[PDB]
Figure 1 (cartoon, rainbow, N blue to C red):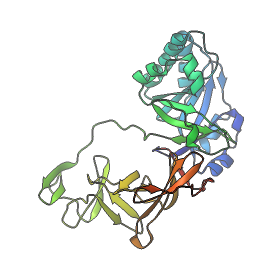
Figure 2: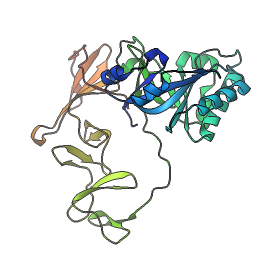
Figure 3: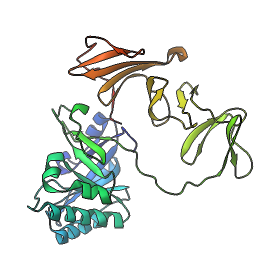
Figure 4: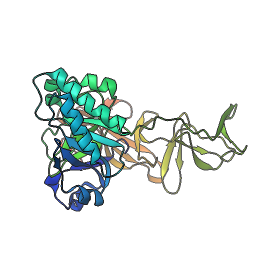
Length: 338
């Protein structure tokens, strides 16, 4: 998954049929509960898996601060993972021992075993519970950006950045449980490896071109190099700091030729590109601020509204906010948090 992608998490509480909530949510991405303690298994697992695209599975911890118990729970969990997924989640939110360090050590052992089995570990919980029972910084020290924190605020079913859990290393945010657990991704999955490199970059007066291993080079086309997309002109030089409409969609090649994805500042205007690099029109919220963007006839426009208090203020591209809010009732656009 990538920044701002959505996913639903379920357990037996959601039943043997979750097609409905996946339709509502608008995604098939899921993190399904497999086990609890060393003796419980979610009976709806196989059905929920069959009906979705799991990106991970979670375990409800009952080991408190007992490392030995944590190890047995992790193995039970592992022994029941039904298919390969990138992530395995440790849901630590109940039965904490009175000793926060012991709690931390138990959680660390649990996560270490998940990593040893070839998966990416995740620590799931609530901020106040985490604040009172573990030293989350010790967890991030061993497992960077591995947090999945729940914080609903009004819990009205929508993502309201105003109540975003403030903590370091948050990978995913469970922003509501109304009517079902809803989550938004804050960071792209890690890919840290060794870029294949199918050629060598060459720079000169005119710019950068790419000499493929066989001596040829891309031109008049898109081409992924080192995991990044670039568009090369008819002469083989990749475009830089430039808009490009291709197949009825607008893309932006940044100063380094890299295709823009997510939010991107062009000049002094903010635009949002989907994971495919294609520009998104209309209302898109970036954290607390709203943007209405259009590209009618190639005329790129970004209307910015900065939040202040309970209102959103229009900002003329000549950096000047109106004296009064343009709106207090947010539009129903795309909500992004990163």
